[PDB]
Amino acid sequence: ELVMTQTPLSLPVSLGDQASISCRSSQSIVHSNGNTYLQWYLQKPGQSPKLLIYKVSNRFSGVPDRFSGSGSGTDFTLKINRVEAEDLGVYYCFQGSHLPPTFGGGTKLEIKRTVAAPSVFIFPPSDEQLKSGTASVVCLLNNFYPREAKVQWKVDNALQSGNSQESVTEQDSKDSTYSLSSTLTLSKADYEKHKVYACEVTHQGLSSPVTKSFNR
Amino acid sequence: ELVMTQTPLSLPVSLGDQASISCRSSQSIVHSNGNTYLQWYLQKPGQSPKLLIYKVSNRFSGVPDRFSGSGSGTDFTLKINRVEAEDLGVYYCFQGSHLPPTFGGGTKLEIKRTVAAPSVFIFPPSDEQLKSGTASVVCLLNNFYPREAKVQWKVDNALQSGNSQESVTEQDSKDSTYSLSSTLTLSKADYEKHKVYACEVTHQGLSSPVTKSFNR
Amino acid sequence: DVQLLESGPGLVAPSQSLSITCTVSGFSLTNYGVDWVRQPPGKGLEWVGVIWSGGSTNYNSALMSRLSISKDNSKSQVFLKMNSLQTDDTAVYYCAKHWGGYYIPYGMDHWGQGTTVTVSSASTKGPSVFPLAPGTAALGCLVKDYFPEPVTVSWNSGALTSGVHTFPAVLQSSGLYSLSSVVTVPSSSLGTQTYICNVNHKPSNTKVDKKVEP
Amino acid sequence: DVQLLESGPGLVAPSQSLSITCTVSGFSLTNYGVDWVRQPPGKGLEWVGVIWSGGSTNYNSALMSRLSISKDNSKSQVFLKMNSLQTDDTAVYYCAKHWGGYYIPYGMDHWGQGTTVTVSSASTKGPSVFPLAPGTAALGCLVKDYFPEPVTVSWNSGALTSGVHTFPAVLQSSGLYSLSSVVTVPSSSLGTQTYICNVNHKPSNTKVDKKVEP
Ligand SMILES: Nc1nc2ccc(NC(=O)CCCC(=O)O)cc2[nH]1
Ligand SMILES: Nc1nc2ccc(NC(=O)CCCC(=O)O)cc2[nH]1
C-alpha cells in the first residue's frame, strides 16, 4: 500500500513570506491512464477540509493565485507565494492513483506575526456554581503572540499546583493570535477557606509578569 | 523533523523466501562525522524490540547472516534471505543522525506456510460463572493457517448474532500458525432456557465444516 | 446548493456497532461517488471507504473486516456501519462528495461538517452552564462536566460573533469534559444590552440559554 | 548481566501526572545513556526522550512541554515524569540502554519488558477467573471483567509452557477486559496431573490460582 510522506510536520512562517510543503509517494502515482491524481487539501481550525489543488497543479475554483502545486512521479510540492493569516491550517496531500487512496500525515502551518501581549482577566466562581458545591476560578489571557505563556495560581500567596487546567485556542485566522484559559478547580469548602486568589501571567509581550487577583 | 518512511506496511512472505523492507528518510541521514546512524529493530509478538542492524549494514551479535542491511544517504533496505518462522514480527528502522531521532512506521512480517486445519474444542460455562449470572460459552480453534476462519454459533440450531466476540493470537514463532477463540455470552436465565450449544467452524484446511457441541 | 450532513449516535460502547448516515442534498447519488474519511483527536485524516455512483465499494485495509458502506439513491443517503468498535475508532467521521474525472475523481469538492464518535463504556452526561460575570469587558460561560464531545456554544443566538473564543474542551480526572466560552464586549453596553450564551449538547439532548449579567 | 525494568502506576486519570521508574542492572548509568520509547496499543514505536550519560536530556517535540527525564546514577534509576495526561498517552512505555559510539549511540542493545500505562478515569478492577473444563485435551481459564490491562497468565506456576495460548484481551461493552488462556495436554494425564492457572493483575494487586478439572 502506498505511503504519502509529507514534510515538514510543522511550518512556522512569517506573514508575507514564501512557503513550500513537500509530499513524496513511496512509488510513482502516475496512473496507467497517464493522469497523476494528487490533491492538496487545507483544513482550517474548526473546519472541514477543503480542496485546493487537484491533478498535481490545477487550482480548484476560489483558490487564490498565491497557491500552486507542482511535481511529478513521486515528488510533489505545494507553494504559497506570500503567506496570509487565513492560510493557517493543516495541509494534507492525497493520492487516488492507487487503491487504497491515502492521505499524507499533514503539515501544520503556523503563522509568525509580531509580539502581542495578552489582556488578562480573572473571574471568581459564579454564585450558581457555588450553589452546587464546586468552585472554578478562571484566568483568561486574550489575544497574544507567541503561544508560549506561563500562568501560575496563588491562593493567599500560596502557589498552587495539581488543581488547574489550561486550554489554548487554535491560532486565530484573522490576527494570528492565541487565547488561553487557565481554570483553577477547588471544593466549595476549600474555596471558602481562603481570601486571595491570584492569576500570575508571564509572557514575552509583557514588561513584567502581571498579576490579576480578587478577594473572595 | 526528519521523517522515516518504511514500506511495505505488511509483508506476507513464504517460508524460505526473501523478504525485502525499505526505509527512506526525508533528508540525508549521513552525519557530518561521516557515519550514517540507521538501525533496524525487530519486535516479536509479546516481546521487547531487539537490535538487528546498526550503522546501515552491521549485524548485531547473534544476528544470523540471513539478515543484511544496505543503502546510503536517504535510501535503505533490510533483506532477509531464507525467511524462518522465528523472523516473524514487526520490523522498524530508526535514525539517530538527527535530533530528534525517529522510528519508521513499522513493517509487519507475516509468514506464509502450508495450510493447517484447526482442532476445535467447545467449553460450557462453568457452574461458578452461572451462579454469578452470566454464561460464557467458548469455542477454541487451535493451530491453523491461514488466519481467515468462519465460526458460527447455533443454540438449539438457532443461528446466533451480535452476542459473540472473537480473539485471535498473533502468528506463532515456531509453526507460523494462529489460534482463535470465539466467546458466546448469555444471561444465566437465557442459557438455562436451551439444550444444544453448537460451535460451527469453516476453514480452508477442512474439507467440510466441523461442528463441536454440547447439551446443557 | 450542495450539502452533506452526517448523523450518528455520538457515543458507542466498545465491542458494539456504529451506524452513521450521510444525508446529501443538491446532487444525485446515482451520479457521484462518496467517501468516508475519519479524523481521530489531534491526528490526521484517514481514508475509510468509498461507495461509487454505481454502488460498488472499496475499503481501508485496516478496517475492511469490520466495515460496510451502502446507500439509498432515492433517499440521498449513504450509510457507514462498523462492528466491534475499539477505543481507536473514536474520531470525527466525514462524508465527502466526488468531483471530476469519470472512473477516478479529481477531488472531493464538498464535505460534511463531520460527526463525532466516542467509543466508551461511560454514559452520556449533560453539561452544567455557569456564567462568567464581567472600555473592554470580558464575559463568558463555563460549560462543565459533560460527556461525550461535542458541545456547541453561541452568543445571542448567533448575532454575536466578533470577540468570541470557545476554548477546546479539556478532559478532567472525573472523565468529564469542561470548556469555557468568553466574549469581549464594550463596557458601556453592560447596562444596556443582554448577553445570553446558547449551549447545545446533542448526545444528552441538552439546550441551555444562560443570561450573563454583571 | 544487563537488565532494565520499568515500574509505574498502571492506571492514571486524565489531566493528572505519570511517574515511571526504570531500574537498571549490570551496567552503570554514569557510562550509558538510556532512551524512553513508547508504543500505543496496536501502533508503532515512538521515541519519547533520552538522558545521556552526563545527565543532559533531549525530548520528543510533541511531548516536551509536558515531559521531564532525570536519573540517579548511584541508585541506577532513570525517571520519566509526564504532566497533563491525555487518553493519547495510553501506551506501553519502554526504557532502553545505549550501545556503541561516543556522542551518538550505535543502537539500543537492551530494553526492559515495558510497562502498561492506561490513561482513564475508571477504577481498577481485578479479574474473575473461571475454569474452561476438559489423545489431546484442551483446558483453559476464562479471565473476565478486569481493568486496566495487563493480566499475565501461567500454568502450574510456569512449569507448563508448551501449547499455552493466552489470547489478546477483548474490551467489552461494560468497559472491562476479558480473555481466556488455554493449554493443550494429554488426555491420559487428566487423571494423574492437576492443572492450575495462575493469573496476575498487578494494577489491582490481584493474584488468583484456579484449579481446572474435568
Ligand atoms: N476521493 C477519492 N476516493 C477514491 C477512491 C479510489 C480512488 N482510486 C482508485 O480506485 C484507483 C484505482 C486504479 C485502478 O486500479 O485502475 C481514488 C479516490 N479518490
Ligand atoms: N538511541 C538513540 N537515542 C538517541 C538520541 C539522540 C540521537 N541523535 C542525536 O542526538 C543527533 C545529534 C547530532 C549532532 O551531533 O549534532 C541518537 C539516538 N539514538
Image: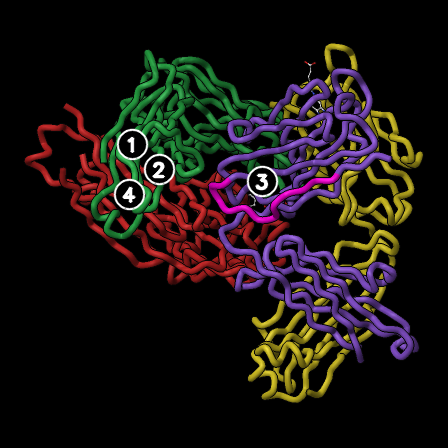
Chain colours: A green, B yellow, C red, D purple
Q: Amino acid at mark 3?
A: Thr
Q: What whole-number distance in Å separates the C-alpha atoms at marks 4 and 3?
A: 39 Å
Q: Which class describes the residues within 10 Å of circle 3: few (<14), some (14-19), or many (20+)?
A: many
Rendered image quadrant of residue D187: bottom right
Q: Tell me the magenta residue range.
A: D5-16
The amino acid pointed to by label 1 is Tyr
Q: Please name which of the two marks, 2 or 3, marks the residue nearer to the observer.
A: 2
Q: Mark 1 or mark 3: name the one nearer the start of the chain.
A: 3
Vertically, is B193 above or below A124?
below
Q: Pointer 1: what residue?
A: A197
Mark 4 packing: few (<14 Cα in 10 Å), some, or many (20+)?
A: many
Tell me whether circle 1 and circle 2 mark residues in contact (CB < 8 Å).
yes
Instruction: Read off the residue under disc 3.
Output: A102
Dot 2 alpha-carbon crowd within 10 angstroms: few under 14, some 14 to 19, many 20 or more: many
- Look at the image and tell me whether residue A28 can be seen: no
Label 1 to label 2, Cα distance in Å?
A: 10 Å
Q: Secondary structure at mark 4?
A: strand
Three-letter residue code for mark 4:
Leu
Is C10 in front, or is A202? A202
Of badges 1 and 4, the one in the foreground is: 1
Above or below — where is A153 with respect to D185? Answer: above
Residues flagged by tags 2 and 4 on a common chain: no
The structure residue drawn at horizontal position 76% and vertical position 76%, both measured from the top left corner, is: D133
Q: Sequence order check: which comes first, mark 2 or mark 3?
A: 3
Task: Judge from the rendering whether residue B166 lies leftward or rightward of residue C160; answer left or right.
Answer: right
